[PDB]
Amino acid sequence: GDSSLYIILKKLLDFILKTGGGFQRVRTHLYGSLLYYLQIAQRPDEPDTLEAAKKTMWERLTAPEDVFSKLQRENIAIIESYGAALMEVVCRDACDGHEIGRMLALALLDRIVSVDKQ
Amino acid sequence: ESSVPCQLLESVLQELKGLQEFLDRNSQFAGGEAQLSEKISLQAIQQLVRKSYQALALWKLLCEHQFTIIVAELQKELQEQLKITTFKDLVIRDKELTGALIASLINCYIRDNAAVDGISLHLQDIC
Amino acid sequence: ALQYFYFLRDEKDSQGENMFLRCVSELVIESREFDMILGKLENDGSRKPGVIDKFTSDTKPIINKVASVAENKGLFEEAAKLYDLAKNADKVLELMNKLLSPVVPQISAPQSNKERLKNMALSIAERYRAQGISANK
């Protein structure tokens, strides 16, 4: 389980919101770690998987598995808080500096994006 | 119907298969005058193991389906000879009857899919 | 598409022939229409020919190529399907055991009695095991 990874994910969000780090270089690292974490959590699965899980829950006929959905929910809560704060930081940042760090931050924004889509 | 059950057929087939593969793999050592006589004897045995494998394989096939109906309709004058056929008789084959029967298995619908292809292969190879 | 690619041979000579082959190979790959293009289900009785097979020949090498690629992507099912055509029986079961093995461990509420990896498991066993089984014990 990438539970241990979860803690790093939290630290990353913390640093970003704080926007400490004179270096965007630092923030690029934070963005990269977050990107992998978001991607890692949902191994490529598509709506079919979600539908199957819901049915199984169907209702807990017996013992269901709803592990991946639960993991996504926890990620999304953490992310929310930290989120408003950090969204501000991530976008402004965007522009400038780092045309570089950019490659990293835009990718982070897009992954995040699916999840927390909605 | 066959004297032996399907489970048993599979068991024998599986076991002989293991032996067949074993000998096939280490055939070089055994084959290739006392030495020559040993060579001949071992060659004969290995051929025998393979032959049994083939007979059992056909039976594995037959077990799948609609064997009984064809048997009843098919058997003619030759039938008495057929019924008193032992496994060893298949081991050391009575080729013509089986060929005719197998042809009927293929000609008729009984063989399904992959099986059918296999007999046609068989008739081609050893028939 | 296959019908059109086949015309390429109409210009008889090497080069064109390879171009044809490459085109078909390219078609199979990325279209991923394996059943249609390559073939399907044994029920003993080898492959049921795909459209290309009707045209024929290099088909085994393409399968290995596609199958390996499936492995990269991790498109299991496609790999199993491809290996069946490849007739790598041992490989099929092994991939198969892996697929069934996970999905077994997990949490409960599943397994309708009609279709999936389990069902897939049933298909292969019934299918291969009776017949001159080439797989490892």
Image (tube, coloured by chain):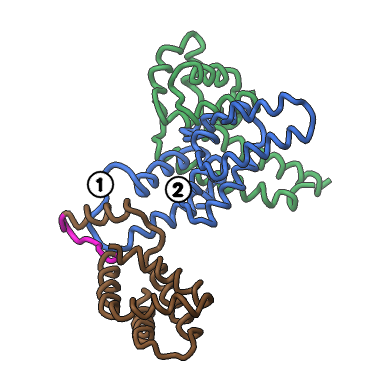
Chain colours: A brown, B green, C blue
Residue C112: mark: 1
Residue A63 in magenta stretch? yes
**Residue A42 placement (x, y as % from top left):** 37, 64
Q: Mark 2 lies on which chain?
A: C
Q: In this view, does C75 lie above or below A113?
A: above
Residue C77: mark: 2
Magenta-colored span: A59-68
Q: Is mark 2 on a helix, strand or loop?
A: loop
* Front position in the image: A8 or C36: A8
**Residue B101 placement (x, y as % from top left):** 51, 18
In the rendered structure, which amino acid carries the disc numbered 1?
Ser
Q: Which residue is drawn at 62% across and 50% down?
A: B22
Q: In this view, does B46 lie above or below B55?
A: below
Q: Does the rendering let one see residue C74? A: yes
Q: Is mark 1 on a helix, strand or loop?
A: loop
Position of the N terminus of chain A, as image quadrant, is bottom left
Residue A41 in magenta stretch? no
Confirm or deny contact between disc 2 and disc 1 (CB under 8 A).
no
Q: Does the rendering let one see residue A4? A: no
Residue C124: mark: none
In the rendered structure, which amino acid carries the disc numbered 2?
Glu
User: Badge 1: how crowded within 10 Å, few (<14), some, or many (20+)?
Assistant: few
Left or right of C1? Residue B34 is right
Position of the C terminus of chain A, as image quadrant, is bottom left
Of badges 2 and 1, nearer the viewer stands 2
Q: Which residue is drawn at 50% across and 33% down?
A: C36
